[PDB]
Image (cartoon, rainbow, N blue to C red; front, top):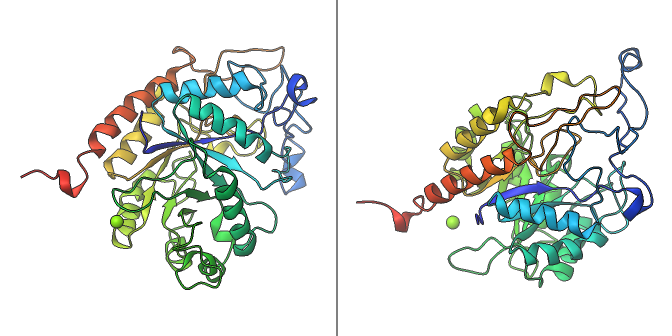
Length: 362
Ligand SMILES: [Mg+2]
């Protein structure tokens, strides 16, 4: 099991049996800002179980995130892929993404099941409304207080010093560097540094210029998230070497994000430019290789189960309806992306052990 391979995990799916209605599977088709364009594309809410807001279809159907055997199945697959950590998409209590319901109440279950399969759970802080340094203090405190003592709570284990909680902060650039420094620098007015709520905060880098803002803010690392090679400066493989050089200089953890493909045209029909065909694993393996070549401290996978953007490595099956041929992993099996990850996890795990200075060869 690889403690340095993280995967982004979503717990926002619901169905009639466990949630009293469908959630997320019935995603609306998103409206292009220009109405002259939007009118040429589909409109309205997908209708599960046969019509869902994904280009692929899961082996578990249009499942519920709070169905305990779904959570267990997911824990199995991750373990079997040799992924040690799930980075759980997180919104504060009684808050949600605009197309979903609250999910913080499910965290205790997920931690218990992760523990059962000896996996760890870190937190992917979403851009909730009015997120700032002040309510980020409160939420870091909350997370560490409520879940910090749980045996599946993730901490990055340094060789010396106390192991630190990790927080991936999606859309960190929305908040100005001077606000972040209140929280993340040593002498900031609401500094968590050297406090019981310290951790490793990882910022999303989109554009190259965001590098400097990230330094000024006091973040401990960067990650790139997007599965589409070429969508952002950060998500382009060719820039990964430089980002790594930058992070090395400034003592930041570089965490590249690798995906198996991308397709979101079931909810963003206009966004065909960011589609990337999986070509039977080749796209994903080009990604993993590019990540490996930078000799990173951690690698992140986008994603376990973001079905809307088609970046999932979770088991998918062929499916056809009277108007839809879903994409699938044929001619390979539903577990293809799990098997490819297991391969590359083991390779990373072996190569990574030779990075450290104490391990360096004569
Ligand atoms: Mg160091």
